[PDB]
Length: 270
Ligand SMILES: [Ca+2]
Ligand SMILES: [Ca+2]
Image (cartoon, rainbow, N blue to C red):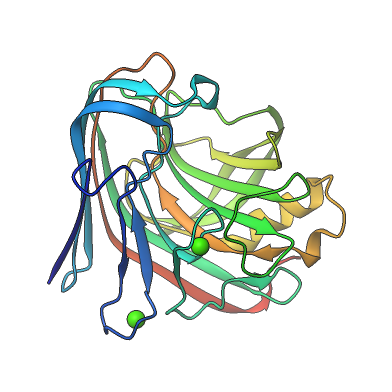
């Protein structure tokens, strides 16, 4: 009834599928994903109670030494749907058929209920991201002619890579109320094209619904990549990037109670 993964007990890359009906196709996949930590004292643990659906992350890391300080953040503990293109983990038991070409995929709402508790000023975000690849089912990383799209609905003390492009309005729902929100749009080239949408009014807890195609449409429109609509939207990842090169301790707790993807009768890109 409770799935648990733990760093460092389960190795340096703990992860596991959430497969509540035991059918061999996960509905989501969880990873502690301390991808830029070389060594730390303490632990990080992610539990997932299969009756309530609560995902709970608890992290107490100290003495942190990074694998590469130029990558800035320490890690991105996360839950995702679809095929994460960096590894062989996937989750496809859901209503949206990911991966799919962006030219074929319906728009969808993403609704997340959550609560974040970073300790002592730790720089963090709460970031949803997707990877857009030239092949349907990538598992070996990302190339220069592909894209990372990130949507930050909370942040403290972190700025997206690259430089600010513009601000956009996106109609979202916060705590049951439809609201026009503003997102800054940032663009970088970091080995691949990077586009991040950073909310101007961070939301540290509650229930948030966003229309995914509002973001992908802007990412398409500002992209320098050729044949953008032939890319596959591989996945939707939800997690908290944290840390900076001068952070040596990182204590953080958070909870996610619901993730829902809701299809809409319309194209993703408009
Ligand atoms: Ca399943
Ligand atoms: Ca994968």
